[PDB]
Amino acid sequence: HKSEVAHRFKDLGEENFKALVLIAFAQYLQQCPFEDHVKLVNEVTEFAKTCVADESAENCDKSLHTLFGDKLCTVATLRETYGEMADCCAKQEPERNECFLQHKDDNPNLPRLVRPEVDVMCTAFHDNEETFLKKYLYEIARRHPYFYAPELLFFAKRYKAAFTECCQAADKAACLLPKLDELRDEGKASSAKQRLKCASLQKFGERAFKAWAVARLSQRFPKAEFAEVSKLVTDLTKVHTECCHGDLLECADDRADLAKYICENQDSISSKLKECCEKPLLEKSHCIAEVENDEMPADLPSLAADFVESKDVCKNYAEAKDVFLGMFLYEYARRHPDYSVVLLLRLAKTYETTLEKCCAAADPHECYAKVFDEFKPLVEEPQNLIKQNCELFEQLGEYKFQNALLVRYTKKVPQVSTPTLVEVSRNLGKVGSKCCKHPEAKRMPCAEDYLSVVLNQLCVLHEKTPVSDRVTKCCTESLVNRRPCFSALEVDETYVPKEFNAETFTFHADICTLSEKERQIKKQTALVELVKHKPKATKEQLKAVMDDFAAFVEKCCKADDKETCFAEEGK
Ligand SMILES: O=C(O)CCCc1ccccc1
Image 1 (cartoon, rainbow, N blue to C red):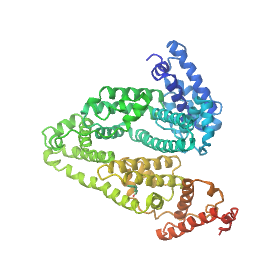
Image 2 (cartoon, rainbow, N blue to C red):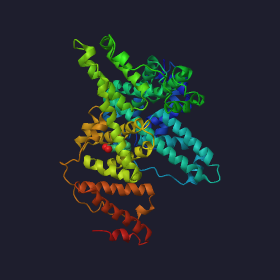
Image 3 (tube, helix red, strand yellow):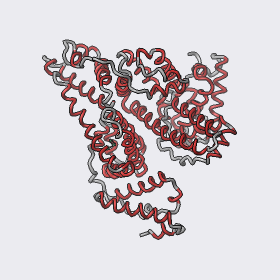
Image 4 (cartoon, rainbow, N blue to C red):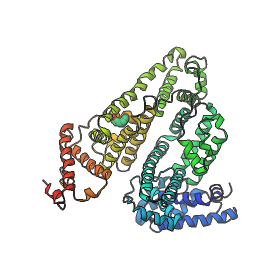
């Protein structure tokens, strides 16, 4: 509009405005205290209200990137707390905003969020409800600087709903802790899922993201025509382009417009949207993003009639390559909800390479006649992977499957730091607990598309301080071949065994007071250090060392030896 901050304030309302601005500052300035961010948000909100009253007021005609960029450099502790980040304010937009994105720390070096007792949180929630929810938006945004901002507003609504219901219950802990544990897990998954959308945009461009969007939406909305799916992909690409670039006010506004358009044209998109569209606005967008795949229309013609057996295959492809390739991806994705997105991208990439060399010959039809037969090896390749990994997971359980994959990937890339290897390998085991129960119909889009997210975690956490060129090679190769690049890696022989440090294998009584999950990570951290020292150690001897450590921990926690049990286990 005329005043951009007034257009977003009037579309989103003050509540969502204040919350999104808070996320914005917390994602860029991740080290500043909570009190300093509230003043900026309130100063932005007071300034925004003056523009709603008069759009032609002072400073109201500036762009959102300019207004947000200027207020960022007003903090006196910018260069003393963030270092060289202040040097980037000497640039105009958008050259200034692009640097601020580079300084977002994916591992921001922040203490773990200790959760107070249930009676303490409930008293604080009743004292100041607005401040209590602001600290939740603040603490999550810092540790997740790319978190899907409109989706974070929804998590805050459920976080508020969990306390409103449970703090009046007779047994508050039995009510609240299950909801909080589920909210944290679903929030970590949402963070990692969105971190791949931004990496795909910031490292491979919109074309690679629109192809991903076309595939998944065609599996999800098979009844919709191509022009309808393309319209949704165009609107969805602009949303995540803004969210990943920090334009959180435009992202949540455009997402609400997109959610509203789908519901007013559901009969042209999908039949699974009747219930999702009867929810409040913030819940409406979340429901649509997780709706089931609609039933594809019955009696569909084969792709060979329009893409292999036609006198205008090369004619329509030459007239518009990406449009013709986008129709092939759409027609194939809608018919195959059992394929993963990344697989459909490989089949489209293969179909593209064939049309580039065959359409230049004199007999194109005889050249690309058997193009679909080249897809058989690509389809069976991830099925052998999932089948072998799920059989290994069903015979060990999640924890032993995590350790099995923890030793496997430590031997592949031993240079990666231990905290990064532990988190990634633990998440590589959670995909087994989530997908290996589905039948072979819905198992591939579950497993392989979640491996895309987890391996992206390895890429971003290694992108900061690279220590291994093997991860860099698989991360910057072609995005869609990331998993095959890692699944084909062998044990790194050029890695020299690390030095021996006894302080790493020394513990205290603090390990007994930790939770069972925190104890597993404490032990798995010691397992990664064991594999680095002896890369050629057999898996059975690695079990003999882990069986002694798993027994030594239980021995010292039961026996009240005043942690002298841990000190005596020195050698
Ligand atoms: O083999 C690898 O490289 C990692 C396999 C990870 C995986 C887990 C569960 C299902 C499928 C795959």
